Length: 242
Ligand SMILES: [Mn+2]
Ligand SMILES: [Mn+2]
Image (tube, rainbow, N blue to C red):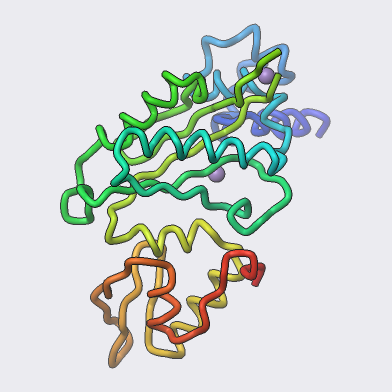
């Protein structure tokens, strides 16, 4: 009812999951002013979401993402040019506006065999924070970081969501592909690959076999190699709507 209407509002909060939104109702937390008066019931994540609830509802204009991406890129280069960093999402596809910035990141040092190099990501984050670009963190794993950022005012920008992922270099490409979408796109493509006897995922492309349950990741060094294995002309991201 007008109360279910309540849980619906909660979940609008980044961090607030249903079961998590639910209990807060059983606590008599419904509107938002409720929540502000009740930070203590919330985790760091949720607190942040709450913190930026408004802004988080606003969309990112690509004139904005552009500058974002430049900042992110120039910072990572200065730390180690051997760093690969690509802003994926519809944004990559040319989208006129975006919801959040999401950066895929890699390094040759780091590969699907290593698997343990937090410092790799961390250093970036830190450099970003030092920059005053990242501004808060919702969470922050060895391999992933979700947070907030903001362009630099000279006089102000909204705070945006940002995600940074660390992928082993031998998996990066697929991943870039993958986070590039669109979803149909991925779908049609894995579909195709399959015709051609190949199985793709966000991590790797693999040849199938008899009975079907098969594989063993082919080497990828670019998105192109993906398309090449499946012998499909290469689609630049803009041409990826489907
Ligand atoms: Mn995202
Ligand atoms: Mn703001």
